[PDB]
Image 1 (cartoon, each protein chain N blue to C red):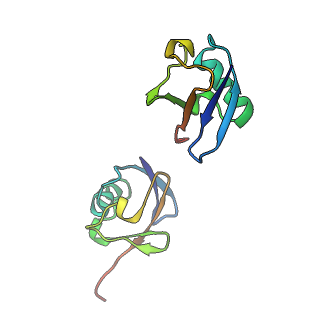
Image 2: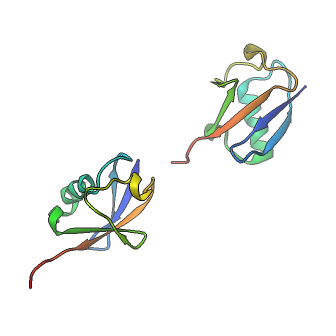
Length: 76
Length: 75
C-alpha cells in the first residue's frame, strides 16, 4: 500500500509499505528520500506520536494515510 | 429473469437480465443503477469470482440467484 509523509520541507513524499511494517521500517524508508537519520525522526499520525516498535496496523494506518515528519533533536 | 446483487452494506439490488447476458452486461446494468464503473466491480456467485466475457448461464446463474458485488479499493 501507499502512504504519504509530509517532510521537513513541507513537500510530501509517497512510500510503498506493508501493513505490518514497523514505524522503524518507515523511518528507514524516509531517510532514503529526505536524508534525515531515523534517530532524528519523529512520526505523527492523526496528531499522535508513533512508536518505533509498533506497526502501521497497530495504529490503523491504511492506504493514503498521511504521516507528518517532525525533527527530534535531543540535548541542548 | 431477475437476479439479486447484494453489496457490502447489505443493500440488495434487483436486476432484470437474460440467461445469455455476459458478466460485462451485468456490470453495465450495475453501473446504470449504482454509478459504479465496471472496472471497479467484482462479482461473486456461490463464492466464485465471475469473468466478464462469460455468461450467466455459463455459471448456472438462474432466476432469483444472488450475486455479491465486491468493490475494488479505488487506488
